[PDB]
Image (cartoon, rainbow over all chains, first blue to last red; front, side, top):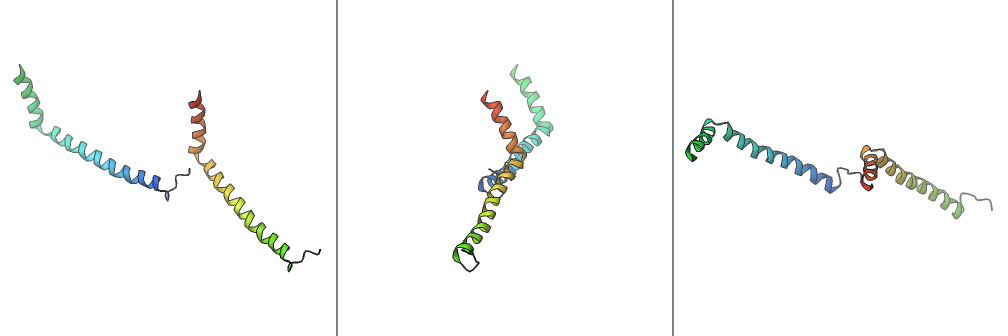
Length: 52
Length: 52
C-alpha cells in the first residue's frame, strides 16, 4: 500500500517512465527536425500546386 | 507463590511482554505511517466522490 522503492511494481513504473519519456521525446524530436528543414515545408507547397 | 525470577512462569511472562509490546507497536506504527501520507487521505476523499 505504501508504494515503497523496494516493492517491484513501484520500481518498474519508475524505470519504464524514464525509458518512455526518452523514447517519446526522441521520436518527436526527429519529426520536428524534418519539419524544421525548408525543403519539407516547400514540398507541402508543391503538393498544393500539384493537385489543382 | 512468590513469583521469583528463577521460576519459569515469571520469566516467560516478562520475555513475552517485551516481544509483544514491540510487535504490537511496530504493526501500529506501520499503519500510522500509511495514514500520515497525503495520498492515503486523498484516496478516502476520492472514494466518497466515487460512490455517489
